Amino acid sequence: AYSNNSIAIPTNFTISVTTEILPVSMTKTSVDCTMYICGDSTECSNLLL
Amino acid sequence: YQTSNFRVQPTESIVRFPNITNLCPFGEVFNATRFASVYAWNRKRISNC
Image (tube, rainbow over all chains, first blue to last red; front, side):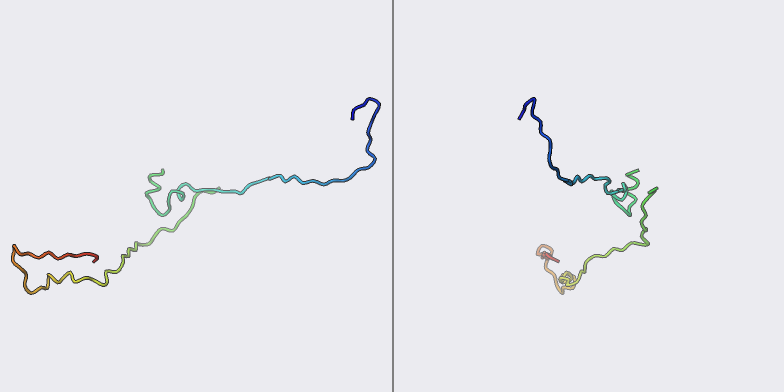
């Protein structure tokens, strides 16, 4: 409702608790280039350098 | 600092192939007593051996 001489004031209240879930950090990962090509072989290292 | 990845290098090489066991008589024509004529020559068929 909309009126100039009318006003609404709350006579009672309530305490509501909500939840927002915010991420902070992710999982730390490190990938090797040589072992991702192959290990225990010099062919991957000479051709990769 | 993560400066590298390590791996132990091999001491020697190992090569193993499957058994040649349950051989076929491939030496039958080698130990045969008498052959045929040069125009009468026999052909030994060796399959799955």
